[PDB]
Every structure is written in structure tokens, then in C-alpha cells.
Image: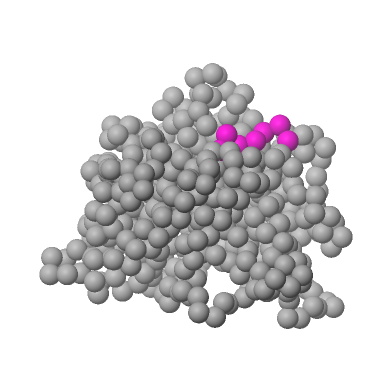
Amino acid sequence: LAFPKEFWWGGATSGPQSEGRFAKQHRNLFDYWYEEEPDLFYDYVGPDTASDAYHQIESDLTLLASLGHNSYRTSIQWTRLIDDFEQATINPDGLAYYNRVIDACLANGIRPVINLHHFDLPIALYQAYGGWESKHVVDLFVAFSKVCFEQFGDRVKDWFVHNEPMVVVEGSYLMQFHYPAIVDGKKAVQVAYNLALATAKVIQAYRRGPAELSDGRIGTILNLTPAYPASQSEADMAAAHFAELWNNDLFMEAAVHGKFPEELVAVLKKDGVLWQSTPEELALIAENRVDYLGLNFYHPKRVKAPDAIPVISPSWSPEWYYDPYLMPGRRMNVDKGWEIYPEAVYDIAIKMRDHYDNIPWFLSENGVGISGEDRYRDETGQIQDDYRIQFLKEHLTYLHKGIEAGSNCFGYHVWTPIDGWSWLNAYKNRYGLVENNIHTQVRRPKASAYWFKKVATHNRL
């Protein structure tokens, strides 16, 4: 079971979740929200210290390469690197921090891969402009990106504009799990649009720059997990087509095909919720397509035709057109109430092959989150997280079958190397290959670390 020459091996993370709030000028939404309602976060642990990567990034990266990693994805937080948002002025301390990150990657044998935005808009832009709802905010985001390209381009040649913008859209405006946690379909569709726009314009800026700061790849981190219909009835079929259009197609098509999907646009319009567009905006989207993509996957999604069609809906939602469906007998991680279905990785792979011009891609995230990990430490104090080895194994296997079937995939990144701060859930469920003890910030590789070393070191299952 041999992976391509050059396969990415490593894990994913973000600034907000690993760094801590050390020395960081601004508050992002999550920073803010924790300060306001600490009681919303598991065990009261917000992002102030997170997994202390502000201090430990060098030792970390030396641990990870020793652990067979050749790539590493984190993010650059707008709230640390940028002093004046309106001019996008550089915070010198932020600059010297992200240089530590990049420099450490290279020193260690590790490909620096960098996302620009991970659920971490600055609170100020929200308060001032309505955040991603604002097309000035978008320009300001453009401004921010150029700085990163200008300051780190000479050594980071792998760039991603967002991690899962759809999750930002749902979190903030539909399901109340990102601040401001309102429920408003119209803003949501408009935010949907603006991130798609901000992606395009960011890609522009990247490609406009000096040949030596624009000779790498740029893309974005999305999702293509299939929405499986409950049955083959035309109606269940129909809910699953919508669930895919919204959840999957919106961004996949903007990024790869330079267009929103005609069908979804037609629906949104019919429902009086289409985004305010601009023909020049639409051209930039068309003109700026990803060199490539990461796709994240933890769990399938299953849907059916709605049990109830409402005459009145207070706010618009894509769930007007489908319901969750639970499949009897499915395999589940109880801790999270999330289905385990590793076959979807293959489906995702074939979906790239057959619907997204087989353009290059990696699984930018994959992992399983458990709690009470304490309980699996053998005599030696090392967590024997067999469940994670198996989980990863089973996903990697299908990833392999996808490659064998022709799927242009070039890497697997585990979410995540060191147990990190999972938002509202904070440290409730651990996902790391390497344990972090959140009191002492001492790391302790788990069984999966050493299993994943073999996998990466021999390029095989």
C-alpha cells in the first residue's frame, strides 16, 4: 500500500488553537467570546494559553520531524501580525513570531503550509463593520494577505486562504457556534459570497506579486463530504442534492470553477436571499481559481426529505430542504455522537476525480476526538490510543483506493499533531497524535505518533 513519491505527511492546526494569547495585540471573535462567556467553554478553558505554541513551536517542530513529519499546517492570525487594520500595518512582534514558525519548519525538514484565516476574524471588524458581512472587511483581508505574502513568500510556497469558510458561515449566522452566533439566513448567504470573493481577491494579490513571492501554490480549505440520501426515493435524492449544493458545491465551484452553482443560485434567488453581487466581482472569481485544495473530513453526513415543510420560517436555512438522518447500525464515536464511515474518503476522492477536473488536492484534515484519554495509559504513561491508529488506518486505506482509482491526491494531514484547543469544546476531546497536558504544557507522544511515524517514514500502510 504505497503512496506517491512526495506525499505530504504531517498534521493540521491553527494559530488560535495552539499559540495562546501571549504577546498578541488584538482579540479575534473567539478571544472575545471567551472573555464574555467563559462558562460556554468546556471546563472554563478558553484560548489564553491554549497549547502554548507561542513558546514551544521550535521544540514542537523538532518533535514532529523526529515523528516522521515532512509538512505542517498552521495559520497566521490577523489579530497578531496586523497593527492597524485599516492600513494593515505590521506588528513587529507578530512578524518575528511567524518567522520563528516558518524558519523552524525549514530548519527541521518540514514544509511550511499556511492558512490565512481560521475562524479568527478580529472582534474589532465585527464591531465596526459587521465582520465578513462587509466588503471593506474583505479588502482589509486582502490587505492582510499581501503582507503575509510579502513577509513570508520567500519561504512559504503553500498557502490557503480559508479553513472551511462554510463553517464560519454556519457558526456565525445559522447554528450559533461561532460568535456573534446569530440566526440570519440573509447575512449568511451574503457572508457565503464574500468569503468566496475574498478567496478570489486573495489569489489575485498572490499572483500580482513579484515572481519570487508568487512562484508557489495557493488554494483554500474546504469540505467535500458527501451528503448521503436516507433512501433512493426521488425526494430523499432531492434533499441530498440540495445538501450537497449548499454544503459542498457553493465553495467548491467558486474555487475550482470560478462560478457559483446555477442551481443553488436559482434557489437562493427564488427564496429572496441571493447575495448582493457585482459583475466585476463575478469576473475576479472566474479569473482566480485555486492552484489546489485541502479537504477536511471527519464524518459522513446523511439526510432525508424534511419531515415537516413549514409555511412560515423566521429565518432562511438550507435545512428547509433536508433533515439529518441517522442510519441504523452505523458505526459511531460516542464521545462526539459522530458517525464513523471511512468509505466517504474514497467517495470524496472520486468526486474530485470526476467533478473537479481531478485538480491536485490533499486531505487537509482527518482525525478522531476522544475524552478521558487518561484511561489508556499503560504501565509506561504512554496513551495507547489504538482507536486512533485504527481510525486513521481505515481512512488512509480508502484514501489509498482513491489514489489507485486515479484521484490526484498529494497528502494526508492528521488533525492534529498536539492536542489543541477545540473552541467551545476546548480540551474536552483530544485529537492529537501527541498528548498535551494542559497544566504543564508538557507533550507526550501517543501510540498513534509512532504508528504515524512508520506510515510517513516508509511512505506505506
What residue is shown at x 66% (from left), y 66% (from top)? 174
Q: Is residue 117 above or below residue 301?
A: above
Q: Indicate left or right for 411 with 245 as reference.
A: left
Q: Is residue 155 visible?
A: yes
What residue is shown at x 52% (from left), y 55% (from top)? 346
What residue is shown at x 25% (from left), y 74% (from top)? 375
Which residue is at the front of the view, 74 or 131? 74
Residue 123 horizontal/vertical position (percent): 56, 53
Q: Quadrant of residue 61?
A: top left
Residue 353 horizontal/vertical position (percent): 59, 45
All told, the count of numbered labels is 0
Which residues are the magenta region? 286-292
Q: Is residue 43 above or below residue 100?
A: below
What residue is shown at x 47% (from left), y 34% (from top)? 158
Which residue is at the front of the view, 44 or 13? 13
Residue 215 horizontal/vertical position (percent): 51, 24
Residue 292 horizontal/vertical position (percent): 56, 38
Q: Is residue 243 above or below residue 165?
A: below
